[PDB]
Length: 9
View 1 (cartoon, rainbow, N blue to C red):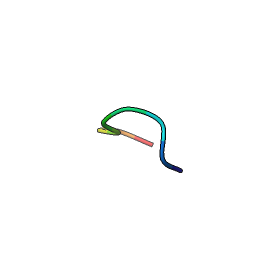
View 2: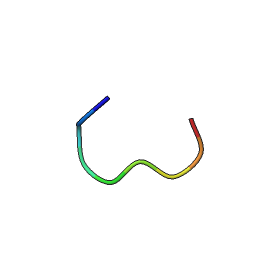
View 3: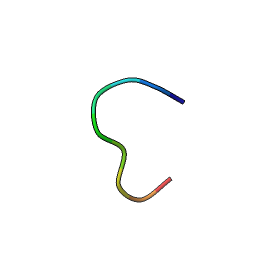
View 4: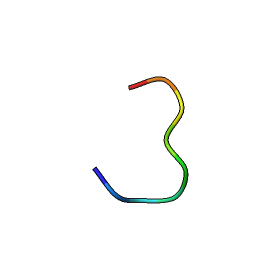
């Protein structure tokens, strides 16, 4: 879930 700044998945 938390990595960098998610947009599409």
